Image 1: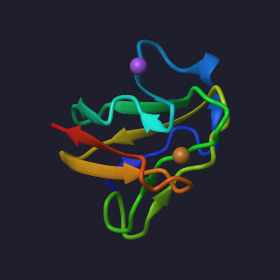
Image 2: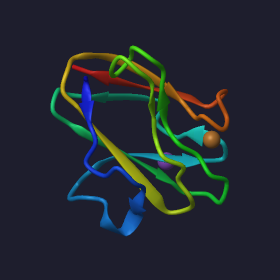
Image 3: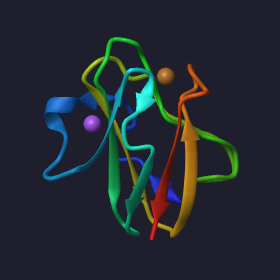
Length: 105
Ligand SMILES: [Cu+]
Ligand code: NA
């Protein structure tokens, strides 16, 4: 697969790492919908609002099957570590019109 998962479950936003690369979720949008990172970087999404959200990569994008992230409540976080260059689109399972991408250089 093209990413690894440091926290299977959502975790508290207060425990986001050291200078972490963060994508905030608010107002039904990923706030940084075109994020550029490098191979080896970890991206952390943080839901800033009451409406639950997740991140969802369709089958084939990060592995043979879809990567459906866990439901994230307000001030919950979820991370993925990208190990291969490429562009990886995602959406919110609950709200598929909400889209973003990670561009890994
Ligand atoms: Cu959503
Ligand atoms: Na912002």
